[PDB]
Amino acid sequence: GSLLKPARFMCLPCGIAFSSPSTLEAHQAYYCSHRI
Ligand SMILES: [Zn+2]
Image (cartoon, rainbow, N blue to C red):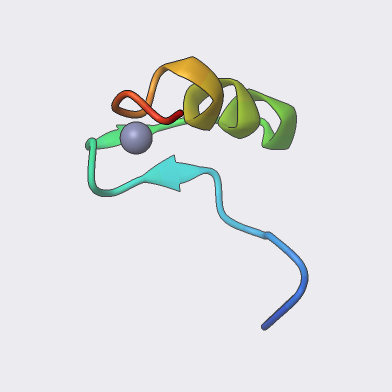
């Protein structure tokens, strides 16, 4: 962990704690704001 290795499944800036790594990518994909 530490760096170059994700180990946290919770979007503090959104206030929604997930329970899966791939799920996080799903949130950051089209759930977290409008990222282009
Ligand atoms: Zn978010």
